[PDB]
Length: 311
Image (cartoon, rainbow, N blue to C red; front, top):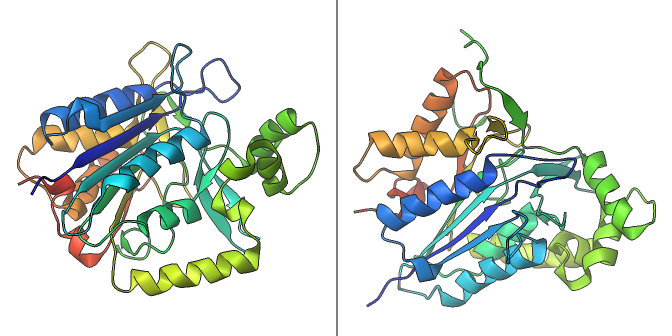
């Protein structure tokens, strides 16, 4: 029985904009070489969506969700398929209505929120694994309702702040709203109005469904999550934190969390549990003076499973 190893790698540098980053595309290229060499992924099973000027497939909100939709077509029940999604780029938090929702910011600002990723993992059968590494600001909780295994509620002298030159991978809500206002030509405080007007069908699930219809849909996910739990989120920081973009525009920049993952893998060649990988990545960032706290969200069984099912 053949098992599939599918990957979607997304990197947003936002070049030549007001929200430029420099290490996100390098994070994607480094993670691609890692899964090709160490984890047995094949070139034809990997989709790369980066926003360099000459890119032919930009990481728009529709292209990202469609690529994640194509891995959703191939995961089968009883096959134990391995799905991987890396995101390096800007993140943001939007008001849930008293509460905030976490989201990633595609290059066209068609936000993908935590309910979109919760809907995605609820389309996967039991035994499948969806490992998501989101090196972005406010990345903690991006898979809504996924149990926190490592984070502020699951873990118990300060280190001097890093001397590296860093830039935040988080955009304020107003910066995201103003960006969408420059495209719609209208002014409203409801970000969903801009997103529905700009993207319509391709807008996030939170913005297309009425709140009560979303409540009915989330009730079906709550029932299914009691028996199937296939989502594994490794966030670069907590829900209330940002993630650091390290370096300048010299072609050598990188994400602090993505680099910490590469360091742990370089120093540990054997198979590593998902919980240990996040813990050792936290140790790297803590020692290096970074104040973001990577978090892990998955089931108890997947917390003890090896990263990307390495034997």
